[PDB]
Amino acid sequence: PELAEAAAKTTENPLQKIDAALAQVDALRSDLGAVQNRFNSAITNLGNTVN
Amino acid sequence: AQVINTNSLSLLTQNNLNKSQSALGTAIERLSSGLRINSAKDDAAGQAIA
Amino acid sequence: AQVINTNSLSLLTQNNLNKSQSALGTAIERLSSGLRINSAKDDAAGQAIA
Amino acid sequence: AQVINTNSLSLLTQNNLNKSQSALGTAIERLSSGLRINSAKDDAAGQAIA
Amino acid sequence: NRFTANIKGLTQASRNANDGISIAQTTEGALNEINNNLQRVRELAVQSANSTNSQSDLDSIQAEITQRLNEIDRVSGQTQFNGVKVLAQDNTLTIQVGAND
Amino acid sequence: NLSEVRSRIEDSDYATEVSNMSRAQILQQAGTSVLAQANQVPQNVLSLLR
Amino acid sequence: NLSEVRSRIEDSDYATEVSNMSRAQILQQAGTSVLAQANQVPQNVLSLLR
Amino acid sequence: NLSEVRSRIEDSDYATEVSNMSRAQILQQAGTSVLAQANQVPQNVLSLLR
């Protein structure tokens, strides 16, 4: 039960809205990409521990 | 210390070859595309700043 | 991590060559015709406005 | 304990040679084909997941 | 025996961790596509702002913006690594990266 | 990315498999050079005493 | 100026990346030429003594 | 547009086919270098024991 609701009225600020979306998205991407560094360092840890 | 059921000399030497393979992979990756940062190349400063 | 049944290094490097091929195709497309917008060059503003 | 009708020393030593033969067989099997999992290489996770 | 168990667990743990990286990369591709769509939307909004653009212009710019937003709804609604919708819902994926619990 | 994950599961890097094949080959040659000795261990005693 | 700053952050000059790829290639060839030796180190002793 | 669609269906980009040919060539050389070993595995044991 969720569909985008027709806009009640023209957006007061078309920028502010898209800067917030880019910040949420950019921030999410940055957060996601640190986990790849964590997994890479964990893999190089487990290699020497297995050896 | 002359064992053959597990050769402790060959395991480390291989790991070094794997590390060199990953370094070659990143260098080919950035040489073909033309760009240093893709995802995990730089986590926050590069991608967010970019 | 030295596999030959599927070379994971060559697949990405190719995709980058394909992307460069598409960029060259659009540049040749706009250089020969003389016009930036054909169809999907600009979706709504360019074509509708044009 | 010096018996010759059945040499109890030779039976175990052979079994170890048979085990080494099976290990060589799997290594040649995966080296020629290029793939680790064929059937019983990994039962469920590898094959089903693959 | 303890060492064998640890070695098995570490390798397998190592084998699962690569998968985590793969999932991150898959999410990043979708995210990158979403970002690309967003960049265009921002530029369109800037173009739309001028007094000069007619309302027949703003209809086409809104048609583009709704198609881009339908597309970033689709590419996040139905994308999956091994039957797992990565962006549809919020949850924690836990990686067993070690033989330890 | 799916080919990368599938590849890890099915494709096996050789660098360990050539070493495993070599270890099994040395174990086979050592096991056969031991087997003959095991075979002749009993005969020396029986014939020598008899 | 924004393209200049963005370019430094994303674009990577090759002149170092071709050298890094070359160093990783020499390290790969040296590591593989060493790996074989490591593999045959144990067999000479076992077979020779046995 | 019909030549574009027909071309995708019939024409095959090489960039993957040279890589597939190279992988099959390495698999052939590795399979033949393994086959000889497989051939000589039995003779050492039989002759050595006999």
Image: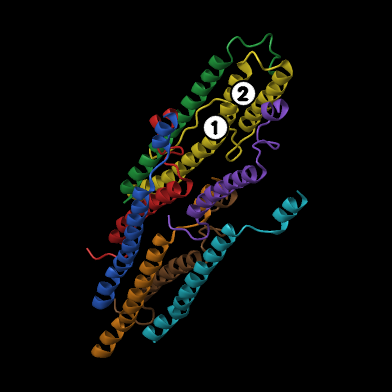
Chain colours: A green, B red, C purple, D brown, E yellow, F orange, G blue, H cyan
Quadrant in which the N terminus of chain A appears: top right
The residue indicated by pointer 2 is E44
The residue located at (66%, 24%) in the rendering is E65
Counting from the top left corner in percent of width and height, residue G35 is at: 32, 64
- Using the image, name the chain to which the residue with label 1 belongs: E
Residue B10: give x, y in percent of width and height: 31, 61
Three-letter amino acid code of the residue under disc 2: Leu
Which one is nearer the viewer's eye here, G3 or F49? G3
Residue behind mark 1: E31
Q: Is residue F10 left or right of residue A2?
A: left
From the viewer's perspective, is the residue at label 2 or at label 1 nearer?
Answer: 2
Residue occupying the point 32% across, 54% down: B16
Residues marked 2 and 1 touching at CB (< 8 Å): no
Q: Amino acid at mark 1?
A: Leu
Q: Looking at the image, can residue E30 be seen?
A: yes
Foreground residue, F50 or F36?
Answer: F36
Q: Is residue D9 left or right of residue H18?
A: left
Whether discs 2 and 1 lie on one chain: the answer is yes
